[PDB]
Every structure is written in C-alpha cells, then in structure tokens.
Image (cartoon, coloured by chain):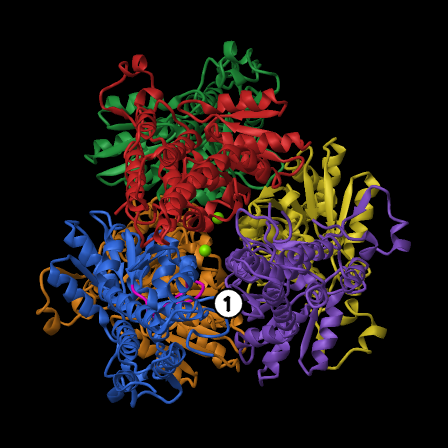
Chain colours: A yellow, B purple, C red, D green, E blue, F orange
Amino acid sequence: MAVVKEVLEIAEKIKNMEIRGAGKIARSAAYALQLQAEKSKATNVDEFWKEMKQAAKILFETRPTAVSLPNALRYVMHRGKIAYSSGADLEQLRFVIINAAKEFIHNSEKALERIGEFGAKRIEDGDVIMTHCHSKAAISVMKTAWEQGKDIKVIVTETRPKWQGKITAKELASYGIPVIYVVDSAARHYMKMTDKVVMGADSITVNGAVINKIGTALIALTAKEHRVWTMIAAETYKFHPETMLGQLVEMRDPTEVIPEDELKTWPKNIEVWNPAFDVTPPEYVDVIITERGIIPPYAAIDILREEFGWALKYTEPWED
Amino acid sequence: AVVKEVLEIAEKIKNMEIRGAGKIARSAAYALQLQAEKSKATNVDEFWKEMKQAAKILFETRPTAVSLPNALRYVMHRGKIAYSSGADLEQLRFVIINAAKEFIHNSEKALERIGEFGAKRIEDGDVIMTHCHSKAAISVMKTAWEQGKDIKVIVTETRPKWQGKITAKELASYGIPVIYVVDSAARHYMKMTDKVVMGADSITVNGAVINKIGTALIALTAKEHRVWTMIAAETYKFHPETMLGIEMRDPTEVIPEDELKTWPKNIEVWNPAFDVTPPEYVDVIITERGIIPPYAAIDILREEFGWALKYTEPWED
Amino acid sequence: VVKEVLEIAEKIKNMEIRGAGKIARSAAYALQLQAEKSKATNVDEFWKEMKQAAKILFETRPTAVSLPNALRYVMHRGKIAYSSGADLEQLRFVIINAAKEFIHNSEKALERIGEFGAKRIEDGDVIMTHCHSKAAISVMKTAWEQGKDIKVIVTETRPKWQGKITAKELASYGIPVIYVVDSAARHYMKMTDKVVMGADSITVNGAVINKIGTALIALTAKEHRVWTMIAAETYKFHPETMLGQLVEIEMRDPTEVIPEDELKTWPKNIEVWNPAFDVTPPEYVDVIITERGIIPPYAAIDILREEFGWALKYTEPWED
Amino acid sequence: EGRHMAVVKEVLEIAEKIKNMEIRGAGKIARSAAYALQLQAEKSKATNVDEFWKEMKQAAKILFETRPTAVSLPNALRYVMHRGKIAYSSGADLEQLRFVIINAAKEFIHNSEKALERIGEFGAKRIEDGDVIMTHCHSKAAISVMKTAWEQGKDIKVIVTETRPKWQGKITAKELASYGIPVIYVVDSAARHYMKMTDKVVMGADSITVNGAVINKIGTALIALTAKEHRVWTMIAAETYKFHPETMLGQEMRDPTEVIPEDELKTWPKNIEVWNPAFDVTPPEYVDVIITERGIIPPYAAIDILREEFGWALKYTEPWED
Amino acid sequence: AVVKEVLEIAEKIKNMEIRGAGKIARSAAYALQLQAEKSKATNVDEFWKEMKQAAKILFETRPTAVSLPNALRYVMHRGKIAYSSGADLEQLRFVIINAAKEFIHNSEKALERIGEFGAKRIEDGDVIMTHCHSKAAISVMKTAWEQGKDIKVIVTETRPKWQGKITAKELASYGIPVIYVVDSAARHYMKMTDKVVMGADSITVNGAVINKIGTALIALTAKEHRVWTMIAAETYKFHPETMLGIEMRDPTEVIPEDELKTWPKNIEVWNPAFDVTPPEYVDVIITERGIIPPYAAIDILREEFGWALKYTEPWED
Amino acid sequence: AVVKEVLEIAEKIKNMEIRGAGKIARSAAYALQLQAEKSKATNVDEFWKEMKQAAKILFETRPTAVSLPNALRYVMHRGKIAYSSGADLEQLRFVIINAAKEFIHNSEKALERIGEFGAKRIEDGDVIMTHCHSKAAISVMKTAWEQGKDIKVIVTETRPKWQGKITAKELASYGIPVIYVVDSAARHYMKMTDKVVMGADSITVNGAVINKIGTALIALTAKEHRVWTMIAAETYKFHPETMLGVEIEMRDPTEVIPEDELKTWPKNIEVWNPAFDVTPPEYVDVIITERGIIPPYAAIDILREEFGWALKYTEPWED
Ligand SMILES: [Mg+2]
Ligand SMILES: [Mg+2]
C-alpha cells in the first residue's frame, strides 16, 4: 500500500457520506485518481499503474451501493488500462490518467447544464409537463425550456412519503414557472392534459430500465397508455451493468410513512412497507436524456461499453 | 299539497344531516312511502300527481346526489306503470308502498349481500389490494375471511384525506392482516396481488367507474398484470349518464391552510375528488343482486329504475 | 293501394327525393294517406291494404336504410294492434297516429341530436370531423351557440371534397376551422379532444358504415384515447351484421377520383377503385348520438327492437 | 515553398451546387459530398499529415454547412471523416492518411451507386408471388423493391395511395404501370378498407430517427398504424445515409396553396386555416423492418447502423470538429 | 305429484344414460313437455305447482351440467310469464308444451344452424385451425366446404386424449385437406392461418370461453397475429356465472398407469381438462340463432333463458 | 500441408461421429490447436496459410452448422489480428494455440457458468417452467436448488419426442419437486409461474431464439403474464444470420404419428412436424451465457466481441 493521503481522505468523506449525490461523488473519485497521478513517488511504468489500481480499489470499496462511483473509476481506469497495456511509458501513462479524470470531472460539472440543453430541444411552447420526486436533471430541462422563452406549465406530483414534490414545486415556481401541485394518485387523471413527462433516475439498468422513487413506474405506465412522450434525464454515470427488472423485485424506515408517535398506536398485525424505488420497464420510456445526448433506453449497454469500457469480459480495470 | 312527513326528510338531506349513499336513498324511499301511507286523495288522479311533487321535492334537494334519484325512480316507475295501465287509490297506493318497502329492505341488506357475492370470488391465500374506505369493498373482505378464507389486504394510503388509515385499522381489528403503502406503491406490489377490490361513488351507462382519485391508476396496473379486478357497488349507484370524455375539492385538504399561505402565488394546488376508471379495466361489478359485467350497467338501469332511451323522468310531464 | 302511396314510391325510386330523413318521413306520410283515405269496409281487408302499401314502398329502394325503418315503425305498431282484435277504425287510428309521430320525431332529429351531443362537448374542445354530416355539424353549431369556444379540424374527405363544404359552413358561423388533407388525421389526433362524425348506417352491433376514411380516423382516435362520437338518427340503424358474411357496399364512379379527361391520359392497366364507405368496428366508437339520446354501440339492437319492433326470429311486419 | 490553397477549388464548387440546389436527391448529394472529400484528399498540396488533416476538416466543415436540412449530406461526411480521424489518430503518415480517406469516399460512392439495386433485392426476398402490395408517396427505394420482385418472376399487384396534397401517387401509378405492373389507384382515405386484402406494405423514408422512427410524407404513419392493426408485413426501404442521430422531426409546414389553390383560397374566410404538414412520424413499433443497402434490420437497430457506418457515438464533436 | 315419465328421464340424466349438452337439454325439455301433456291437474295453480316440482327434480340430477338448467329456464320462464299474467290451465299447459317443442326442435337444428352461420364467415381459399373435436366447429367447416369453398384445416393434436386424430379423419372423410400437427405448433403456423374455429364446453357471463386445455393458448397467439377467431357454441352452453379470474382429469390420461408407476414420487402429473379463454381473444361466438360478440353473451341469457338480476329460478318459490 | 489430426477430426465431424454444440466446437478448436502445435512452416506467412487451410477444411464439412464456425472464428479471428499486426511465426503459433485453449476450457465450464449466472436471477420459492430438455436450462435450476432455494419446476411434456419425461425425471433426481403437464397447458399454469427458463438451438443476430417447437408459444404467454423469461445458451450458439426478412427443419412425421398408425390414414391428411419455433427477442428478457446475462438485442455484440464477426468483413480464414 503506497497511496497518497489525498486519496485516503476523499474515500473517507465518501465512505462516511460527507460527499453525497451521483455527480459530486463521481467527480470526487475521479479527482482522487487524478491526485494519485499528479503527486506520485513512482519511478517506473509499472509501479505507477500498480498504485493507480491500488487507489481505485479503495475508492471503489467505500460504497458498494454508490452508482456513479464505480463508473468514474471505470472511466479513468479503462482508458488507463488500455494506454497501459499499449506499452505506454511512465510519464505517458500518467498523462492519460490525468486527462481522463480531468475530462470526466469537467464533463460532469457541465452535466446538469448540457442535459438541460438536450432535453429543452424536446420541449415545446405551451407544453404541460408532468414530473415526479425532486430531480435536478429533470428540473434543469424545464428551467432551460423556460429560459428559452418557452411557455410551459409543470404538473408536480406530491411524491409521498418524503414529499419531494414540495421542493420541486417551490423550486420551479421560484424561477417563475407556473406549477400545478397534485397528489400522486392523480397522475392518470391529469395525464390527459400532459404533453411531456420528464423525470430523473437513481440509476439505469443494462436493459435500459429505470430505477427511481416509487410511483415513477406508475406515471410512466399511464403516460404510455396516453402516448405521452416520456423522457428520463440521467447522467451517463448512472448507467448500471446489472439487471434489476426481475432481480430486485431497498426498504426504508416505515416511520417515513406513518410517524413514530402514530405508528406505535397502531395494531400489531398491520405492516407498513416503505419501498424506496420501483422499476420502470424500458418500453414505458421513449428516451433517456444524458450529458452526451438523447438516446433510446435499450442503448444503455452501448453507453456502458463506449464510456466505461464494459463488456462480458467481467473484469474491472483495477482488477486482473 | 305535500305532507310534513316528506319535507321532514328533504330538509335533513338538503342540509347533510342524513348523509351516506345508502341512508339517503332509503330516506328518500321512506319519504315516498309515507306520502302514500298518510294521504287524503280522492281517486288515483289526485293521488298520483300528489307524489310527483314528493318525488320532485326530494329530487331537487340534492341533484348532485346519486342514490337520491334512483330511489325515487325505483318506486315512481313501478307507480307510473300501474297508474298508466289504470288503477284506483288502493290499487296504485299499494304498488307504491310495496315497492318503497322492498327497496328499503333491499338496501339494508345491500352491504351484507354484496359481501356475500364478492366473497365467492375470493380464494384462500388471496392477497387483496384496495383503495379509499368503501364499506362495500370491506364487506367483501370481511366475508371471505369470516368463511375461513386466509386473505391478506394491501391498503393504499389514499391521499389527500388518508382514508387508508381508517381501512387499515378497521380490517386489522377483524383480525385481518394488513399491509399499508403509499398510493405510489400500487404498481410495485401489483406483482404480488391476486385480487383488486374497490368501491365506487357511481357507475356510468357505459360501465365506467367514478371513484376516489387514484382508483383508475390502480385498475390500470391491475389490467397490466392481468389481476382480476372487482368493483363493489350497489345498484342505486348506477348513473344513466356518461362521465368519460370533474369535482374539485378544498386545496387545503392536500396542503394545510397555514402551510399553503407560504407557497408562491404561481403554484396552484388541484384536488380532484375522483378519476374515471374505463370499463375495460374492470372485470365485474358486485351488486346486491349479483355479479355483472361493467357494460351491463345499461341493463340494470332499465330493469331496476326503468330507464329508456327516449327518456323523461317518471315524476314530470 | 291508393294513389298517393304510389306517387310517393316513384319519387323515392326515381330518387326524385332523397336524404335519410326526407324519404323516411315521406314513406311514413304515404302510409298515413293510405290509412286516411282507404275505403276498406273490413278490418282484415284494411290490414291487407296497408301491407301492400308498404311492400310497394319497400321495393322502391331496399338499399336505403331509413325507408324500411319508417315502414317498420308504422307497420310494427299496426301489426301489433291488429293481432289484438282491433277494429277497422282502431287500426286506422293506430297507424295514422304512429305515422305522424314518426314524422314529428324525424323533423326534430337534427336539433335534438345537436342538443344531446353538445352536452358532451366542453369549452376549449378541438373537434375533428369527416365528410359533411348534418347531424355532426348540428352538434358543433349547438355547442358553439351555447357559448362554448371550439376549434374544428375538418378533414378534406376526398374524392368529392366534402371537407370544403364543412369548413366553409362551420367557419361562416364563426367557428374557427383547421382544414387538412385526410392523410393528416393521425398527425393531428394528438391535439384533438373529440371526434364527431356522421353515419350512413349503423349495424345491429353498433358498427358504423360511413364515408371512406371514417374508420381510419376512428382507428387513430382509439390509439390516442380520443372520445369518439357518432351522430346518427335511430332510423339509420340496420338489422344487418358485418361479423358474418363479408359485405362491401357500393363502388362509385372512378371519375370522382380522377376526372374523365385526365383518366384517358393514363395507362390501361391502372384501375381506379372508389369505395363509398368503410366499416368502423363498434370498439372504436364510444357513443352514438341519437335523437332519443346517447347510447353505447352495443345498445344498437335495443333501438331496433324497441323502436322498430325488429326481431331476430320474427318476420317483416308487412309480410305474410 | 509549398504554397497552396487550404481547401481545393473542386470542393468549393461542389459545395456551391449543393447550396444552390443544383444538385438534389439523398443519393446524389451524399455522393457529391463524399466525392468532394475524395478530390480534396487526391489534390491536397499539403506536406505533412497534420496540415493535411486540418485542411480535410476545413473541407468537410464547408460542405456540412451548405445544407443543414439535407440529411444524407452529413452522413457522407461522417463516413469519410470518421475513418480518416481513426487513421489519423493512430499515427498514420500523409501517404497512409490520404489513401484511407480516398478509399473511404470511393467505397461510400460505390455503395450509394448500388444502394437502390441492393435495397431492391433485399426487399424482394420478402415479397411472394401473388402478393398485393400497398405503397405511399413516390419512393425510388420502395419502387425498386417492387420492380425487382416483379422482375424475379413474382406476379404482384400494387395498391397505390393517392398521396395528397401533391398527388405523388399518380407518378407512382403511371411508373409502376409502365414497367408492366398492375395498379389499383386509391384515395388515401381507403388505406384501412383495403388493408384486409393487402399482403405487404412497402414505403420509403425521408429519414430514420435514432429510435428507428420513420419520417416520411404525411399519411405514412396512418397507413402503418392500420397495417399493424391487421398484421400486414410492413417494410420501409431506406439507404443507411438517411439514418439520423436525432429524435422525432430533428427540425415542416408547406405552402397552404398546395392543398387549396390560391384562386380558390382567396375566396375562403380567414376564419379557416389550411395546415399542410409535409411529414408525419411513424413509430418504430408499426414497422417490421427497414430495408437497407446492407440488409434488413429491425427498427431499433437504427442506432447500430449509425455507429457502424458513421462512427457515431455519444460525443460532443463531429469527426471534422476540433 | 310428478308423472312417471319425468322420473324416468330424470334418472337417466342422473346416472348418465343421457349425456352431452344437446341430448341432456332436449331430454330435460321433453320431460317438462310430458309433465304438461299428462298432468292430471284440474286447477291452474296445482298444475304450475307440479311443473316447478318436476323442474326442481330435473335440475337436481346433474347440478353442474350446463345446458340442463337452461333447458328448464327456457321452458319454465315462458311458463312463469303466462302463469303470472293470469293464464288458465289450458293456456299455460299450451305455452309450456309449446315452449318445450320449440326448444327441442331448435336444439335439433342447432349444429346445422351454427354451421351455416359460421360458414358465412369462411372465405374461399381460407385456412382454418381448430382444436379438440367439436361438432359445432366441425359443422362450420363441413358446411363451408359443402358450399363449394376450398379450405384447408390445420388440426392440433389435442393432448392428452388425441381428439385431434378423430377430427382429422372425419374432416378428411368429407374430402377436406387436413394438416395434423402437435399443439405446440399453434403459434408457428398461426402466421398461415386465416381463421380459428373452435368449440366450447360453456360460455361465461362475460363471454369468456371454457374449453379443452390449450384453447386459450391458441386464441392468444391468434389475437397476437390478429386472426379472426370464432367459437361455435349453442346458446344453452352460455352460463350466468363467471369462471375467469376447473375439472382435474386422471393423470393416467397423460402418462399411462403402466409407466407412471416408474417415475419418482417427487413428480406430479397435473391434467386439467379446461382453461379459460378471455373474451378479448375471441371475435365472435357462433350460435344457432346468430353470430354474436363475446360481450353479447348476457343478452342471450336474457333473451333466451329469461335471465336477469333476480334471485330465483322460474321454478323456485 | 494440413496436419494429420486435422483431417482426422474433420472426418469425425463430417461423419456425425462427433455431435453436439459444445463437443463439435471444442473438437474443432482443438484441431486448429494441433495444426499449430505440429506445423512445419518456415515463416509466418506460410504458416498462416496452413492455418487458414485447416480452418476452411473444418468449416466445409457442415457449412450450415452454428457452434462449429464460432469455434473457428474464435481462434482464427485472434490469429488474424496477430498476423496483421506483424506477428512473427512463433508468436502467431502462440496466439493460435492459446486461443484454442481458452475456447476449449471456457466451453468445458460453460454449463457450470450458465447455471451460476442463471441461479443469481432465481429467487427462493420461485416456480420455474421449462420446455424440451436443455442441459443449460436444467443447469440453472439445479444450481438454484442446490443453493438452498426452494423451487418447484413445471416441466412441459414437449411433443412429439417427449423430452419432458427426461427433464422431469432428471430434475426429480436432484431432489427438485416437479410438475409434469402437457404442452397445451402452458398458459393455464403461467398464472402461477414466477420465472421461465428454456434453452436454445441458436440465437440470431437480432436476438431471436430458435428452439424446440412450442417454445415461442410459452414465451408468448409469459410476456402476457409479465413473467421474467430467460434463455440459457452458450455464446457459440449465436448465429450471424437473420430470420426477419420458410421452414427451418421438417422432422420425420413418424415422431408425431407412428408408421403403423399413419399408414392407414388417407391422402387428404398430411402431418407437419416442424422441429423449431422462432421466438421474437421481445418475448425474452435476458439470455444466459457462460460470460453473463445479456439482453437479446445484444447478440450482435457477442458475435462481434467474442468471435470478431462483422457484416462488412469476411471470415478470418478467407482469402
Ligand atoms: Mg344489450
Ligand atoms: Mg447494439
């Protein structure tokens, strides 16, 4: 073990969750690799690649759950592993790893903006838009469309149990966008007057299925039933290599639904389940809006391939 | 030319003292009965037009109500049929009182009988999903279980007013295991649901179901999962009109007045009471006279309340 | 039969008078005169004068639908009376009476249909229509006159261009019109709230026979979940089926499509087919707007039975 | 000394004709743009791979900007440039790079020249003797599939839809009739009525979206909808360079007088607005296969064509962008 | 007070000397005819009282028989109408006797009639895929062919009892081209099938069809390929209840006893007799009175067997 | 200059002496391995020629088979990359030999791996339905059962050859509770099925599955009931062909109706015994290969990345 202090610190903040959010986390791990590369005591082209992998394993293990973390690492390590086994020199390999990370970081910092741009192109003047939860990426599409002078109205679903809809209603209204706040159970009733559906995603599966706050799949279902164009705004680093459509089907604190004081006063045979997400089938989603462009759900695997060097080779860049 | 025994009820109905689909329809019937058990009518002619007022009276107390005009249509139809065919005082006065009593009884045993029919469609081990707080739907659940059927109910929260808490506590008290979830979880758990049993506010001539907001979403994913879906609704909830192709409630029902004051002026809170569930998303409707296909609603209107295409209320010109 | 009966039949055969309503009313009028002017001295002798009277009108244009219905309406009621041991005068009365009743109702049909349909039109509704249906237009004018702000998308309706007539007519009343070629029906179904069309005839199951193009529109309306209404008088309901033997209605003159001049400029191996109608399955029709009220398509048979005494098993009222 | 103009005159000349529209058609344009890049590579006076590559990118940029509405144009550019960008980045020298580019363009032009014939053959594999085929508008690719099947000895009858407002069906009817193919001319409204006696639907395309959706003349989607309703095998004949990386339109209202002649329309109350959309969008689910010069593929493989043929991927720049 | 002949026919239906939807229906009806033709009653009320007794006894032989209750409903419905309208002994006796004859004659022309109605929907050059061995369905094919139509029939094996072999030879006998294949080949050959014609054991109140296992599978792929799917069934096979949302035959039908003895005990050979085909997967039902949409099944229960939202059968108090 | 053992195995293969997807594959790979291990070439160029000739000799034996050519592509594609890159004689031999060995090893542990991956997607209590007799499919269930996961398996008879009996008996042995039911009952029991797992005779470039007749019907109903459906198949079963835009293989009619009984049937009757069903990729959630689970529409990527196939290129042993 010969990893820099910088790296060890970043992983500490990640492992303890001092750094949260797909974007910030990914940006952090990429930057950690960048540090291990800039300030490295190495001397040969193998000692460097070795310690580079040493670092990536640590960062990786801070949170098995974290979705964007593994990808930021794969992004930087795949290009590195390719330049490496290409016979590249020491100072040569270092350069590769630094620009890969720096390019990742920059790309990520601009992620929310570019997604907004790409999604706004699919937003028309007079469009009534329905959304769910509190998604920065989705909100960025609506905001950009409004800043382009497009006259839109956003139907915000409450999003029980944590009510993320309130934050979304207030945030959107703050920019001056007309908002209609509604209970989740009303998504179908108003799908009849919705032109576009724009939601975010915790992660995307290899089949292009969408993992997001419960209710999401319900909205997508009725949107599909009404031929309402449905877009999912998500960064490339949220694309996941495994299946979840029939492999997962995370349970959260039951008290999020029924308050502690209230829950204890309830019968014993009544059980409160509070599932965090549901899985939206690829067929219920028209396109996924990423920082690199709009793509169809089933193109998810191409993203995993082109971006993070994924393949059934089933071996992580920092592995062998 | 109306008895106080009538306006006696109309008042409470018009003022909400007598509230409930069942009770309101029964009182309306009872009213039309008294005017037939305490009336000073010479012959059948002064008698009939004497009730057309009693019916029209109650009819205008709450045009909004659904079970209100059906109760009236029930008796009055069987009255105008005999009347027209020709009848005297004690001839028509009879068919009237007779019908009113039947309806009233048929109603008192409604929830009981609906549970009966519904239970027959419930199997041991059936996981059941429901919405809002329907006595009709709950009766079905409570009967299957009281027949020795091992059922487990998934109760949806049912925002904005949380009728789910009521349904959850009530069912658990009967000793029925309950699983409480937010409305948004309806699709997620539809995968492990066997039967969907919900109530109704009203039913349309096409067999469409008008019920608390969210009901159509559940029915939509039930159909997506080929889950047998039943709507427990008594005959007098059948409307002779179309609703497919809107009743906004108090916005503070969703966001409290004190909290809603803070919110920006460009944020409106919409609180629709119901949504409309298409007949194709409902397998059968459980009435107190049997189980029927949704689109059979038009037949119930004809048989039960004497509805015909070229129509005119049975208590008018 | 008398003379008036005969002089009306020719004005029907020679089609010197047409229009679902006009001929129906005229057919009923004839039977009325036969009743009002018959010199029959016997009841059974009178019943025979009516049967022959009707048989004569019926044979003028079997193809016509309203005709046999006007006769059925009047004759079914006459036949019933007769079988109850009704006298010469009671039957004459029953007939004359039924005839005038049918005539009156037919006279108020367009108006009543207009009223019934307008109740199903909301302020701000975009309505797509096809051909030039007096019944459909009546629904639109009536809604507009109730103060409802509507915009009507009028389909061109080749080959005879009825859309032009409808566009000019609706626009003349102040109703904003969008005129499009038939091929754009799907394209604009996305901004349509309601579809209102007429019918040449309705089948025993609620299937609609109307001007070529109608079924395509209804097809895409079903695809977009757009409330579809057919405006049609009760006497347009036929006891025939479309689920059984394959029946394709009249083929019209090719020159309606390609004029004679242009047509002799074409290669001989090109045939110009010009079907008048197509069939809309009852599954693509939400409601039919009749002068007696709104009904689901599967109630069509109820109209035939209760209104025209038709019976799957029974015979024609003026037969035997 | 090595004095010379960066972009060669031939390129500016070809670009001119495409800009002035002197050159038209998805094939001809794509062919001319590719040929320009070929000439640039054949006549460059550069003396080092870097300068050459730079001039190459200048050439493409000029061509790309002639018509941002022409769909085949940028794909001809991507085909040649993507392959040049690869050779270039891989450290190839002037000679090697010139060859790669010149060879790619020749390859692209040859494939385009043979595209109609090949689409014709791929489409015919799916046509059977006695088949009743329904078409729309006037598509050379689609017509090619029909003439090819008819020439393989397969008797077919073609139901030609009128295709208003511009009446392209008349052109299609006369043309098919001329090759000796029996034709049934019909109004657009009759599509569903005759879909029951139809075996195959073969239409063309103006462009194909990333999702495999089809952009074609108004009415195409309607026909496809009723074909699906009836399970009639539906094929869209389209060259690879018509595949686009965008969604839906990727951008059209034509002149009202195309539908209602001016002399008659000046007679109509302003109260009536004549809407004449050029295209409609056909969902990939109403299309069984797309017939390409490289073969038959399902609609959702459109993204594979973009990648393999035009080195397309989720990048921020085009192969000729710095 | 039932007459000898009624107890005789009743016993044969109970011990099954009389089997089959048709024979059981015509027999039950004939029994009612006899009770009415030989009744020794002299009072209209005593007579009707007998008819109900005789009907109750006939109805209890094979409770689960489909057409049995309907044969009784047809006759007894027209009987309760005449009676309740105030008919005299002679008149009621005539109505019942007339209603039974009508039903029996109708049932005897059923196959012929169904065949004719179905054939109208069979174009020349059509390819038909069938299942099991249904006289009704085979009647449609035999008829179309007899009308001079060139059609080919694809016959599915129909495990476990190979009823397909019977249908094949039979059809072949008439000189109809036949294609025999395993059930599993349903979908693979759907692509070449113009129309699907199959029989039915019974039809539900929703228009769902109950028939030999596999029927619903064929109907599913048929709708997948949008092929016209017809179900040939007699009106008396329509039942007032819902099944969708059955009988388990002996495993020996699948794996012979001789061999099933070998197999490990941790294996179970399930052999259901029927499956439930959703009305959505069937276009029309071919009846002896006409071609109807599955959803029009309720109009047949009403129009033919006087079925309504009542609680009692025409022979019950 | 084709080595002895090469013409040797190419004989066993063309003579059906050797049969099976895996076996004929590994065997074909091996052949190329010996050709490389015992070649008498002076330089690379002449050696490659020998390799390209030994390959074309194995290929021409059954030019329509599926596993075989994928075995050849696996080794030959890797050899061409080397050769093209300027690989010297010994190097190229090394690449060839080590590629044949990867292919053979990977192929020997194919079933274990597939069962290992498929098992990850099988939950405790799950009811699995299958068709025909698939070692790969069976391997998944067995692995799940041996994982402690309580599972029942509905086995479909699978006429006309009754492969269901074999599968029912086999799964029984491992101690797995089986439910035998005729083909016609697939839908009736899909209502209680949690997962569908079947095999494949091959996979097309578009992800469509070619398998024993009746396979498409089951996937059809499984799509209707939203039951997670899985197809277990070796990567070398992917075939660079399309079914999109005739009969695959008509088997002897006697498997359906015996000669003794058929001989008595009239001319009018004609029995058709298709061997395969074509299952659309839309009715298949994932394919289970020795390298992991993949969506059907990714079949083209397996052909490209595993066997180096590309529509615009020629087989690695051509020219
Ligand atoms: Mg009805
Ligand atoms: Mg791909």
Amino acid type at circle 1 is Leu
The percent coordinates of residue E73 (x first, y second) are 38, 71
Q: Quadrant of residue B11?
A: bottom right
Mark 1 — residue? E309
Task: Inspect this view and state whether residue D199 appears.
Answer: no
Instruction: In this rendered view, identify the residue nearer to me: F307 or A1.
Output: F307
**Which residue is found at the position 56% from the left and 50% from the top?**
A225
Local secondary structure at mark 1: loop
Magenta region, main secondary structure: loop
Task: Inspect this view and state whether residue E49 appears.
Answer: yes
Q: How many numbered marks are there?
A: 1
Residue most extreme to the top: D263
Q: Quadrant of residue F178?
A: bottom left
Q: Which residues are magenta?
A: E199-211
Chain assignment, label 1: E
The answer to whether residue E239 is above or below residue D205 is: below
The percent coordinates of residue B98 (x first, y second) are 61, 69
Horizontal side of residue B86 vs F133, given as left or right: right
**Which residue is found at the position 34% from the left and 79% from the top?**
E271
The picture quadrant for ligand 1 comes to: bottom left
